[PDB]
Image (cartoon, rainbow, N blue to C red; front, side):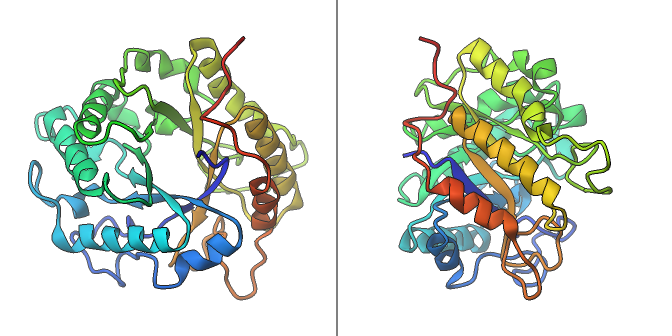
Length: 321
């Protein structure tokens, strides 16, 4: 099945400056008992960021035993707690700061990583889908469509069933999506289970930093307006979609109303969402929905109302008929 409501569980990708880094200091995986709270809340789908450099400290080589094993443990816990997991290679179309398709990082290396990820985890019941690359941007944008096909090819060697989530250029911006997306039309999936995944935030620059409050001229439909370009492109081209990130601060009711409006529109169009973000070690992060003493997380009550609604049969939008 495809859940319309889901959350990001971030932490494994933290502190990029430290490689390999130390678990519990630089990066964090969910502790025992972590998924229970979310499952009891009624959330059953999770997007899980991973750092490519930690998974694969050398290109075209076996996955790291310690980091990959932590992933195994996390998947085992998700399964015990009725949680389905989207693995996200959270890398901006780069390995050690070099773009995929450059001489340092050939597309074949990216294909190799995807083959390895699919080979290791295709047998795990808790695995739901592969989000093959988080937020290609900048000098990566031109070379990304070629890289994406290599990633699809990589996964499909070992997993011919599960959905592939394909992000777009320009930080996978939903708002700007039609400006660049046509380059993704040449992508082909032999299994016909390919879904585009866009990101959206409703602060002024759409970065999710929230440098300002809503302001006097705030529009409740701002989230909907920002995803329409994406959803309309999907409709025009007979493609399927997904919102892999959206988040808001807990300090203004107006943000919550905009979120409600966005969720209604996504629900109408059968587009699933992954809220950014929950996680084992967020501290004071403004967008966090993880429980923290003294913090209310109104975003969670809102997600719960939607989670109760019927899922769609498949990733939308529904085909014209």
